[PDB]
Image (spheres, coloured by chain):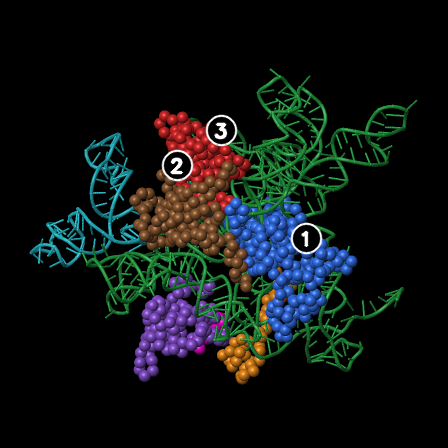
Chain colours: A blue, B orange, C red, D brown, E purple, F green, G cyan
Amino acid sequence: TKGILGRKIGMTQVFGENGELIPVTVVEAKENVVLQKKTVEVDGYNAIQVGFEDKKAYKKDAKSNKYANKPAEGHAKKADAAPKRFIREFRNVDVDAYEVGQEVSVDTFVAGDVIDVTGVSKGKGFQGAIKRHGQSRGPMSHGSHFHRAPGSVGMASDASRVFKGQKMPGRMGGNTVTVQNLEVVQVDTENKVILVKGNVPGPKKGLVEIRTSIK
Amino acid sequence: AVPKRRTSKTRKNKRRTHFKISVPGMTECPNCGEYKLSHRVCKNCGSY
Amino acid sequence: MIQQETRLKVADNSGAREVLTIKVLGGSGRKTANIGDVIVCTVKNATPGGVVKKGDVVKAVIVRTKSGVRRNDGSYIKFDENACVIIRDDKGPRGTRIFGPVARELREGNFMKIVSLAPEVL
Amino acid sequence: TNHKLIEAVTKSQLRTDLPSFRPGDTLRVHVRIIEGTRERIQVFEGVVIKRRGGGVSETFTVRKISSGVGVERTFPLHTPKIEKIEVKRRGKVRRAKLYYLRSLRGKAARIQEI
Amino acid sequence: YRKLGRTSDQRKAMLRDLATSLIISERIETTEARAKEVRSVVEKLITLGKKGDLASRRNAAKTLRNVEILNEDETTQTALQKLFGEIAERYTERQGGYTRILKQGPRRGDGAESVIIELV
RNA sequence: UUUGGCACCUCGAUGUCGGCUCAUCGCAUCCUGGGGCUGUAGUCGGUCCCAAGGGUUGGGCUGUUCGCCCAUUAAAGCGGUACGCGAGCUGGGUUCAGAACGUCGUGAGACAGUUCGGUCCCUAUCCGUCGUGGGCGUAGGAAAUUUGAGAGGAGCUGUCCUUAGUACGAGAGGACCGGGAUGGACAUACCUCUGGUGUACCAGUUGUCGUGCCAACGGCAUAGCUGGGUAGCUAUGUGUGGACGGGAUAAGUGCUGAAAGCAUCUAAGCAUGAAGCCCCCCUCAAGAUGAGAUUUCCCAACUUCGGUUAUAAGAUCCCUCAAAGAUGAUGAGGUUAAUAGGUUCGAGGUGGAAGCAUGGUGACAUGUGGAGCUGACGAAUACUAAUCGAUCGAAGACUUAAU
RNA sequence: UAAGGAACUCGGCAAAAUGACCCCGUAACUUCGGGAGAAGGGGUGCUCUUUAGGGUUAACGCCCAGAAGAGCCGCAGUGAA
């Protein structure tokens, strides 16, 4: 249960009890609202839909995603709310505890709550096997002409082919990844921020989904 | 390293289906002269 | 950060001066050791007389590495050289006189005799 | 605002009782040791080698020589494990990072006062 | 930042050559990327000229090349003198800008995006 | 999987051994797991059965395959895949030209018994693999949020404290069962800390040429060298993960119970039972042609609204850019505007500018003054540029049954 | 390029390190020539004094100094090659 969205701001450190140092990620969880409530009798599964960051109203002759379109405006009109940048669903919550139009406030979370955090990895691009996987590099001396290539990719006439999942070069970067069992250090309601123990995936000013751990 | 079979006309012209030129923008010069290139005050009578 | 083939000064009066390390024990694949960790080693340069003689295979505990240690308060400590003390397979030393300073992380490994014999403990 | 959040959130973890010092100055750091027995206190006297960082991530390093062996100790500036800092002596140096002291001994590793 | 397909010293020298020629002529024809880089250089030079002090004059002479202009009325001055006399007076009240890029069509020998860059 | 026998493909060429890189399969199980028996008191051990999920070290002497040794480890398993892998790498071995020892030979020369030395080519057409786009489809057209048929990944293990010096044991020794903290290796994310780099940042310094000279600056000397270092990228740094739990089962233990008045774990029935199977965890996923679901938006003037000029919702061309990136995509923005630049102010970095004055014979020092300078980081400000525009874009069929 | 320092590999292959000038000192073994530049140590910038050398010498001045003192700066003075 207890899901929210936020933007990654950066990393700092804080001091706990008995002077211990705690590296911390600060997350701006601001103006989250509920836009829709999906149900088993209608949509086939219970979930709420949450919108996080407000954008500009509809405008004729608009070219960017800073300005809402007519569908998004109508969707955010049912709930007496503004249009939002990011929309995500949460299935882990109890659906009856929330109401359409409700504001999801950061004070849902309190210190000591263990959480899971989801986000897209940073982005690196076309990378080789030494970096994209943990492959060893060949000798750099003694007559070698094999440094950063991948080695053999198959055996021989028997299996005259390459199997799938052979770990070749390619794009490495943004894929969604959760880290499990991080905890909340404190909450500041006036600036609407959460402090998470550790580090979370993604670049700065990037979306993160915080929710409660199962275990 | 070398091709084992020659390439047929079919395969060649299939490969050559994305090998072409796009069309430019051609915002017609409201000021004067020939039609201006978009976001370009063209040397040949453009007023972008 | 002590791996295989590193050389360490010895900080006791057991008889050895220089020592070469053969193995970082613990688990399989253990590559590097640091303060508080036990190693097996050879004596490459000994003092005349002394208990231990050149060519002997012995066990030692690492004290005062150069790539030192972090602590839970975020403090760090480092030294200017790497050193060790030779032990009697009971966390006790073969010598009776420790030299130089010693880290405070030895208390967590039950090396109280070395900590007591030492000068300044940091 | 999106740029003052880190400062605003880490303002409370910051200390004000610390004095001003720069590299070269000789410091006496009183650090509290919460051993298994009690909450003892121990002093560490040496020369400031390195100051760096910002705000709460700020950090400084001091160096001394105990028994013929050089010893460097690095603290966060705003940690509560430091009871007290004293500036015993002021130095004269033309450099922000005194890494050249690591390969000296004796009168060569002496610093003019003021 | 841009490397312009050149080494560090070649890039530095070409940038200050571009800036000097622009101070001389007040509009020049070049490529898009070179213009987008020399823009900041010449703007900082004009900022120094507006400050006017001796130290700024020296920090600008660090960059500018020593070139003589044939001014009207048979008069002669340097690019530094022009920068600190006229170009600073023209923009004493303006806060930023000072340059405008105007795109043109591609060249013949290449397909390079040609551009004019002009003082304003 | 050996040494061989045969001589069926290949002599208009099917690369020989070791080693490196990269794997994948089997079980005839090295460790971990579960059990029966024991000439198993406990601690252990031996043997047999089940079982392939994961894991299965670094060095010395070896060309060496093989083998011996040193130190660890929970363990240092056996095999197959052209004795896996040279259009992926070496080239130590053997064997080509040179030369030498020993032996043999009248000799030219030979042995294969030794020894020193001795050139490893290839711009990927098809299949295949790793990524990433365009077109069309999915009974109206679109924006967004999703279900999950399937698929992939993950799966290891130790030491310590207590139970308890208790059970057992003459004693030495010494538990099961359970509870509790920390580690090794591996994988993943990130740069707050520690450090690396940081060729448009700051300082010091040598030679030489120039700016008429001084001074200051600039050029070349690996970025001339040296000392530091922001953003970003990073590990050796910082965090997180797995040993859980449900079902069904193997070996095996059983309950009830006949066939066969007894007995029997089995035939019918009821239970328990493993790191193994499925689910649970993470990720991809309606090209899932079976093409799915929810919310919202739009709808023609003629017109079998077919075809039409139109056109709407919505996209795109073009342009300023980066949290993205080979290109293309992706995302942030396009004057009702802070997208980039500039400007101003900061942060951090360097470490005390110039000029003036004073002191000193002079090299130099002190003060004005945490000075001055500052790439990528942050905020603010429309000074500059993101112009005027153009294009594309639908008209919810038929059949039956309900209504 | 942190820590480590041949653990790589058939093999320290390659790279790193040494490197100029001045002074001090230098083994075994030798065919007495050598080895030997053995090894191994130390020093080098700028300024003012001079008492004074190569002397520019006419003389300290004109350059290196006989090179002896006294100072200045810097992480580093054959500060690069």
Q: Is residue C97 above or below residue F278?
A: above
Residue linked to disc 3: C89
Q: Amino acid at mark 1?
A: Thr
Q: Is residue B39 rendered magenta in the image?
A: no
Quadrant in the picture for residue C94:
top left
Pointer 1 and pointer 2: residues touching (CB < 8 Å)?
no
Q: Mark 2: which secondary structure? A: loop
Of badges 3 and 1, the one in the foreground is 1
Q: Which residues are magenta?
A: E112-120
Percent across and percent down for residue F43 are 62, 25
Quadrant in the picture for residue A73:
bottom right
Residue linked to disc 2: C100
Percent across and percent down for residue F186 are 56, 44
Is residue C6 visible to us here?
Answer: no
| Label 1 crowd (10 A; few <14 / some 14-19 / many >=20) | some
Mark 2 or mark 3: name the one nearer the start of the chain: 3
| Label 3 crowd (10 A; few <14 / some 14-19 / many >=20) | few
User: To which chain does the residue with label 2 belong?
Assistant: C
Q: Amino acid at mark 3?
A: Asp
Dominant secondary structure (helix, strand or loop) of the stretch shown in magenta = strand
Whole-number angstrom distance, CA of label 1 to CA of label 2: 57 Å
Residue linked to disc 1: A1
Q: Amino acid at mark 2?
A: Gly
Q: Is residue A28 left or right of residue C18?
A: right
User: To which chain does the residue with label 3 belong?
Assistant: C
Percent across and percent down for residue B4 are 60, 55
Is the C terminus of chain C in the top left, top right, bottom left or bottom right quadrant?
top left
Q: Residue at x 64, y 53 (%)?
A: A211
Q: Nearer the viewer, residue F163 or A71?
A: F163
